[PDB]
Amino acid sequence: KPVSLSYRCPCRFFESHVARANVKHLKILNTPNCALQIVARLKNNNRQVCIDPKLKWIQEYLEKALNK
């Protein structure tokens, strides 16, 4: 069977509404054949989700992470 395997990404979707208060750990994963995937694990849900870079607290996060 001819099967086309795409360049697999750690994320498929990105959460577009995440609470900083519910984030365990922030991890941003740039992937050579994929988009810029942000990864965060939830505290109350404890599941590791994906985050969209254009979130408001995320823009702040990137800015202040680069600023320090």
Image (cartoon, helix red, strand yellow):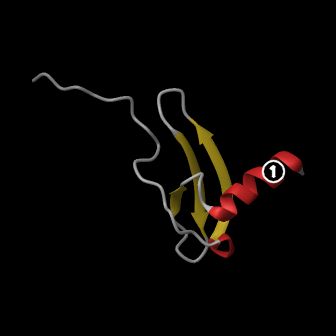
Q: Nearer the viewer, residue 38 or 5?
A: 38
Depicted 10 relative to depicted 34: above or below: below
- Which residue is located at x 52 percent, y 74 percent? 45
**Which residue does the numbered mark 1 point to in the structure image?**
65
Amino acid bearing label 1: Ala
38 vs 18: above or below: above
Instruction: Return the residue nearer the eye: 14 or 4.
Output: 14
Q: Residue at x 67, y 70 (%)?
A: 20
| Among the 4 quarters of the image, the one containing residue 57 | bottom right
Residue 17 position in % (x across, y down)? 53, 69
Q: Residue at 44% x, 38% y: name it.
A: 9
Residue farthest along the right direction in this orientation: 68
Q: Quadrant of the N terminus?
A: top left
User: Which residue appears farthest toward the left when viewing the image?
Assistant: 1
Per the image, label 1 sits on a secondary structure element best described as helix
Q: Position of residue 29 (x, y in %)?
A: 60, 41
Answer few, some or many: residues within 10 Å of disc 1's Cα (few below 14, many 20 plus, some between 14 and 19).
Answer: few
Question: Is residue 8 depicted above or below 51 in this figure?
Answer: above
| x 51%, y 59%: residue | 49
Looking at the image, which residue sits at the far top?
2
At which x and y percent is residue 50? 52, 55
Relative image position of residue 15 (x, y in whole percent): 49, 61
Q: How many numbered circles does the render carry?
A: 1
Q: Nearer the viewer, residue 29 or 64?
A: 64
Q: Is residue 61 left or right of residue 33?
A: right
Q: Quadrant of residue 60?
A: bottom right
Compared across the picture, whether 4 is left or right of 6 comes to: left
